[PDB]
Length: 79
Length: 15
Image (cartoon, rainbow over all chains, first blue to last red; front, top):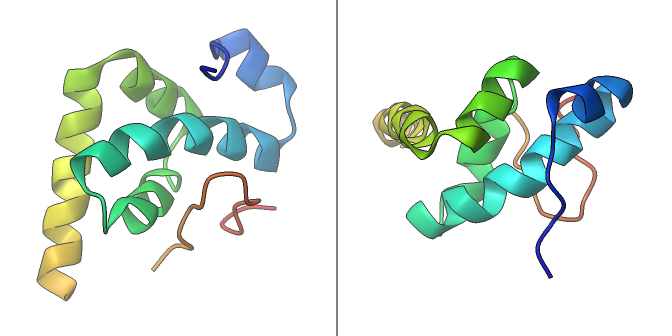
């Protein structure tokens, strides 16, 4: 079954580690669809940034793709 | 450089 919908007010009520977990559980599968091997690394990189921006990325496929693309470029240069 | 995220495992990047 699908994970539940995440809103700003819901996210805001949770402890800091829990907010990152809420965001990560939703980001990971979408990122993994794009980059099966780097998914874990990409997701951890993205979780470094602000939760309200991460929530926006979850609400806008275009926004998530753009961020993923930058993270991959960075990882590929390092590897 | 940040810890990888693994579904269903507590992320160690902030805890």
